[PDB]
Length: 303
Length: 297
Ligand SMILES: [Cl-]
Ligand SMILES: [Cl-]
Ligand SMILES: [Cl-]
Ligand SMILES: [Cl-]
Image (cartoon, rainbow over all chains, first blue to last red; front, top):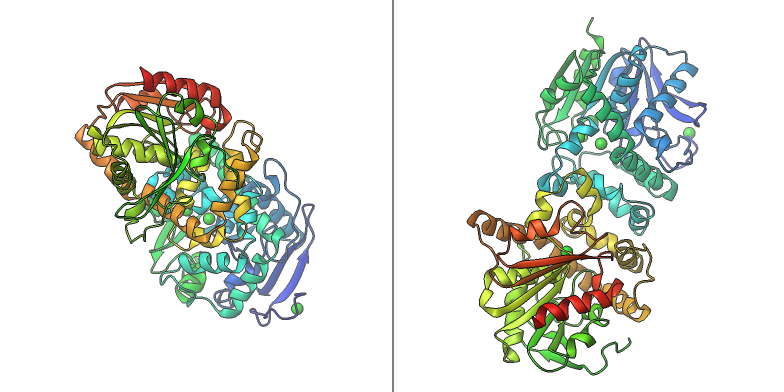
């Protein structure tokens, strides 16, 4: 990268700045074999995969991308409908990025916001995917449908960060380090930062220290309250199911299981889905790296 | 800070939980007015004079708000539950010899008010609540649309110190954004600038902001459970009641306010006022006449 004091958490992996019509996508690229794209979420960057990507690179050509607007990827200017940070637009952009590498059909694993890009990609463009894995999420529509007093208090940030600009931007900008560390710790099993490599945390903190990066994150959640929700509602009410073979992995103490049985939910959205919990909080690839890596290796390797 | 209550004195009223500050004016039957979030007693400055033409008007800062003392909170946020606040204000009124009085409240103060009516109806001759539904009714309506509309009910109720830390960055911005965004105009032009300064100065103290978060923590937990018991018991406020709400306020957002209150009260009348949330400042003339006519009748 271009940040002198941030650590290289993928020894041996190359680096790519991939041009697209919507801006550059940064990625680390390693391994060889069938192509597998990995997508991080909030409030993280591509380095969240640093503990599982080497194991995956033993069997796949692994592409670890920063989401549009996150990490070192470019930050398109948003609009009144939060368009570039909708999962539909993010998926189109990452499809464009993968074509630049010559990948028109690939395997895909996503976590948190990246998992939302991933199932939206499967709904809009299923021919692009051989197999899909989503980590510690339910569909955005399903989160909102479960909204009640208990859900609103337990996962408040969906409604907070979706408030009109500049309300979340100005609240997060007073003490950004405290917020990003608080969010990282609060979703782990133990409720502290012990699950994370401190060098990865510094990546997350430096990203969050940029007000333009924080604005993108709020736009992500604004799309998640509005367009993404409207997009999802159209699919579930039409009975559209993802046909791509799918794996749902969630943490036993994560977000997706808060008030739902995740595999039953995903069977409503996908016609060929398997799933398993893992004893972990929300951050599966850092809290339970070996079990996550093995589940992904076995799923993506299965004939 | 400006004096916005001509002809009103200023009183510090002792209670077992700390002092209650109040402006006091007028003569005649006693009437207590209770403000809400993020304001102080000065929010009544445009209607209290007309009320003081007929009543002894007592304009109090809520426990922990404005210039009233801040009792220490606990793990169930007890002193800032509306049941506790009502008890403390009942004590303050007894210091003045008022054991039967009329009551009007707005926002948090309206929640103190209907809880007071449910707990101790003998204290009230009449009750007015401005731009609210019962706390239980907000939470039962907390779907996607409402969670986005009143996000602060969940945000300010997050465990300390998350909202405290975020509010400390730019407190002037937050109090001004809450005031502006709930009015019809969406700016601060409906408020007297001197009144806004009162609100800003109070919000500038981290101890006052913590109390407000404890208030919203009570609203998500104990207050909700207290309301739920009354719902399950079929309890209705027997005190004659007035529900005023802004046509573009919060109470009307996801519900029909008079239909809701008639499930909570056996003798309630009401009307919308063309106004956002802050009835006594956005629409002082219509609010004052409605209140005068109700508390005289
Ligand atoms: Cl480098
Ligand atoms: Cl998410
Ligand atoms: Cl979820
Ligand atoms: Cl309120």
